[PDB]
Image (cartoon, rainbow over all chains, first blue to last red; front, side, top):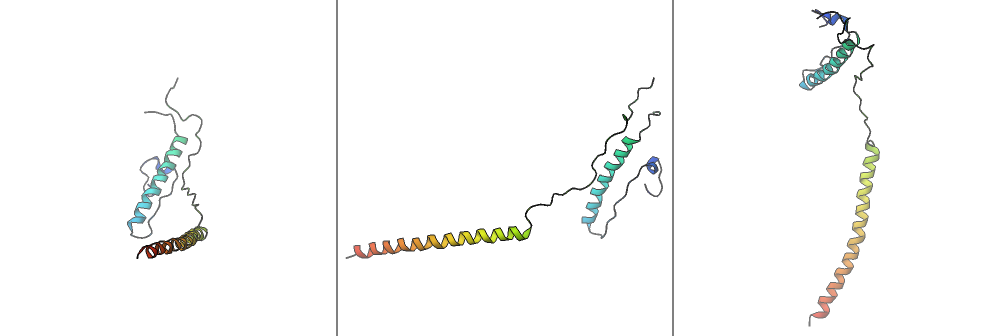
Length: 54
Length: 68
């Protein structure tokens, strides 16, 4: 999503979490903060929605 | 006319962050109240077992004076 935006992902703004060790505790916590960023993307997507065309 | 479902004039912000109240009387004070309640129980235990030894001596006097 950050490297090759294949869609309108470029016009929305977020920040992806990164794990610090290989410990799956970090992996779990990365999943949780990706969920919270998913809520941010949904918030901006409801903010800037165009009524264009199906 | 156009009658899609538009976002109606912009939407309010949605909370998007962790929030931990983190209270609970940190280890100093609660460590203190634990040792204090423990000491309270100790002192009551001391007083009650002394009274109990008094009663046990009275029952010993009963078995002594009964025996012959």
